[PDB]
Image: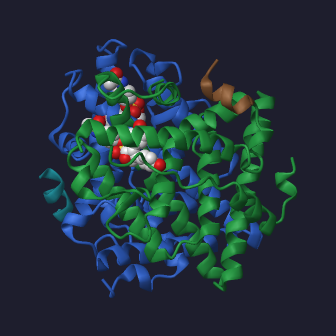
Chain colours: A green, B brown, C blue, D cyan
């Protein structure tokens, strides 16, 4: 595995180049079904970019297909959410789903159970803003989510070696986060404290994902909003 | 068979 | 608060306060007349969790910095973290029993026992996997009480701002204590921030287990499987 | 609120 041989700057350099673009929403051709239509279409196109971004995450392509499938099935909504939170940092009180789709609590209230999750996302974006989260730290956190969010739900000495490789890449990303903070001028104590603050926020991103996944699976049962074939398979992974 | 496995294998 | 004792405590005083605040290990009911069924199983587990909640509340009041919060904020953190706290304690005491969950000294269940309850085996596997992960890491007692206090302070700090800064200031102190524990244990500076990361990443999976467990505990209420105590009812109503 | 009085005691 070449991921283990990369330096800290090579790890950052690799992840930055793999960054997917910020996609646009279909604009002004608003009901509850219409906003759910925009969000589903938007998230649907982001999944295709996320899948190809995962193949560029160092160490990810060194796993079996089924382990690669498993990690994405588990983290995909977390990865979409931390993306939304990141690009919404410069818009206090706003969620920048897309440069042409700027929403806040005023739209979240016309979809049942969505304003609660909107408040949590905004608090996360407010938190990243108060912490002055950097682009290099962001790509490290997103890679951590991909590799960690499903590592303890895997199912042999071969499977244990694959779980062990994931923990080796995770240690490599942790070293990279510390190198970034050390290069920024933070003391050794400030490095450990900031590393801890960033990683605890991931627990809140997991929480927002589970809370959101629960509503998304009830939306499939209602059959009122049509979700594409890829989204229905990502939803069935969490209900199973 | 999964579309994800289809997309990851390409 | 700025006159908090948590901020004035050293790392060794932080460990000692947390160790002396440890709740007691309770026993399960042992009524042999009840059959081995979903209703009797959930009745045993419900009763144990009910009694553990009363001791957790006293423990929370002895967590440094917790008494400094308002009564409403204290209620928020416990309502948000109570299942996470019960789960990590169960995982901690199940370390000496591979492949089994030690709910109580007189109640040591394995993966198969929960199969009369839909979804319980899946959560048992996640709890068992976390226990084996803590064992593989050789999790120490001093690290356990730090992690559990982190759960109490972090899990709800973003869903409710000088009190926000107080919680984060206490969390930074617990980060210091964790590092001091690992340095005193003789780990290198690199192994320190890597192990800190590994421990904090497991907190995301504990949140994931709590979110899935809370969803099942709510459906159990809505199915009248067992009677629920009024305290447990208010704990569940906080999540829906 | 049961959780209220349990915290005061
Ligand atoms: C009545 C009803 O249907 N309610 C309800 C529905 C969904 C809820 O999901 S979300 O957690 O708000 C969920 C998080 C965010 O808002 C929703 C959404 C989404 C995602 C997928 C999708 O297919 C639809 C929406 C989002 C999102 C989209 C793209 C992105 O890059 C980041 C986040 C919550 C509540
Ligand atoms: C409703 C249904 O069909 N199934 C289903 C039911 C419950 C499930 O709870 S658990 O998440 O397994 C949940 C985790 C663990 O087993 C269950 C349980 C619990 C908690 C509260 C309670 O009132 C009852 C049980 C636990 C627990 C208890 C004490 C403790 O110190 C640590 C953990 C899961 C699935």
Vertically, is A61 above or below C163?
Answer: above
Choose top left, top right, bottom left or bottom right for residue A216: top left
- On the image, the x and y values in percent for residue A168 come to 77, 51
Vertically, is C81 above or below A219?
Answer: below
- Say left or right for C40 vs C14: left
**Measuring 33% from the left and 48% from the top, which residue is drawn there?**
A28
**Measuring 27% from the left and 35% from the top, which residue is drawn there?**
A33
Choose top left, top right, bottom left or bottom right for residue A65: top right
Q: Outermost residue toward the front?
A: A29
The front one of C31 and C47 is: C47
- On the image, the x and y values in percent for residue C85 come to 40, 50
- On the image, the x and y values in percent for residue A14 come to 76, 59
**Measuring 45% from the left and 66% from the top, which residue is drawn there?**
C18
Q: Quadrant of ligand 1?
A: top left
The front one of C128 and C34 is: C128
Give the total number of marks visible in the rendering.
Answer: 0
- On the image, the x and y values in percent for residue C205 come to 52, 45
- Say left or right for A61 vs C6: right
The front one of C182 and C158 is: C158
Vertically, is A234 above or below C183?
Answer: above
Q: Is residue A8 at least partly visible in the picture?
A: yes
Q: Is residue C95 at least partly visible in the picture?
A: no
**Measuring 40% from the left and 56% from the top, which residue is drawn there?**
A100
């Amino acid at each position: 595995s070449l991921a283990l041989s990369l330096t800290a700057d090579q790890m950052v350099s690799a992840l930055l180049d793999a960054e997917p673009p910020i996609l646009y929403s279909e604009y002004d051709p608003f009901s509850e079904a219409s906003m759910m239509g925009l969000l589903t279409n938007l998230a649907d196109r982001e999944l295709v970019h996320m899948i190809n971004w995962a193949k560029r995450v160092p160490g990810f392509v060194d796993l079996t297909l089924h382990d690669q499938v498993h990690l994405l099935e588990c983290a995909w909504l977390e990865i979409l959410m931390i993306g939304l939170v990141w690009r919404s940092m410069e818009h206090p009180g706003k969620l920048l789903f897309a440069p042409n789709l700027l929403l806040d609590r005023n739209q979240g209230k016309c979809v049942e159970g969505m304003v609660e999750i909107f408040d949590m996302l905004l608090a996360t974006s407010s938190r990243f803003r108060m912490m002055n989260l950097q682009g290099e730290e962001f790509v490290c956190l997103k890679s951590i989510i991909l590799l960690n969010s499903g590592v303890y739900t895997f199912l042999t000495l071969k499977s244990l070696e694959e779980k062990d490789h994931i923990h080796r890449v995770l240690d490599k990303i942790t070293d990279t986060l510390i190198h970034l903070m050390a290069k920024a001028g933070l003391t050794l104590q400030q490095q450990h404290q900031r590393l801890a603050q960033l990683l605890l926020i991931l627990s809140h991103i997991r929480h927002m994902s589970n809370k959101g996944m629960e509503h998304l699976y009830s939306m499939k049962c209602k059959n009122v909003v049509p979700l594409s074939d890829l989204l229905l398979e990502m939803l069935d992974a969490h209900r199973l | 068979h999964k579309i994800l496995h289809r997309l990851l294998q390409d």
